[PDB]
Amino acid sequence: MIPGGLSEAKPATPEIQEIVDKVKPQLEEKTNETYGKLEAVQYKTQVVAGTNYYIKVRAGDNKYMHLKVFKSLPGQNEDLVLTGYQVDKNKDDELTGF
Amino acid sequence: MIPGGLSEAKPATPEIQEIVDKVKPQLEEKTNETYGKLEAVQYKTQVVAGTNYYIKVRAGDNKYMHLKVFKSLPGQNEDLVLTGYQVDKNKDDELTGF
Image (cartoon, rainbow over all chains, first blue to last red):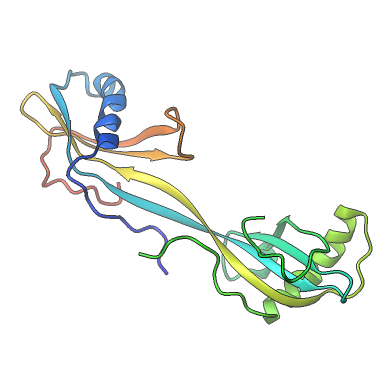
């Protein structure tokens, strides 16, 4: 529906305490100051989306094609670009990040 | 709310037939192979995801720091890049478009 939404805010995780532990040297140079005790507090997560397109197409009873087109901006059909494409495999071929 | 996965399979939309019609010459040039008639059949859509992070973590002497870290691919410690940070402000500072 809506790409780019914040997840639940967790008050501290083992990964969040690891993020501060990696960011303390870079933050210390940019702040001109030493931070005291670094303890995990509360993080959220935003997921960005894009749109990849996978098509099944009938060549005759002997052949059947898959197609793969990347799109960026909606409202322009000419922005469709072929980035992947599968062969003569049947309609039984499931379109699965091929 | 919803897991990733391909969208609904439409058995030959007017967009599906237009995508294969435009990719019929490009498929035959890239494979060097001649295909008979390509008619629309069933396509599915594909959702890519990217993950930005918004963290709070109290590293002050008496203070609280809050920073967001953008990452590309998971399983890489060098992929975790600090792009945005907050200082000595408390848990009241919400990580918002940042």
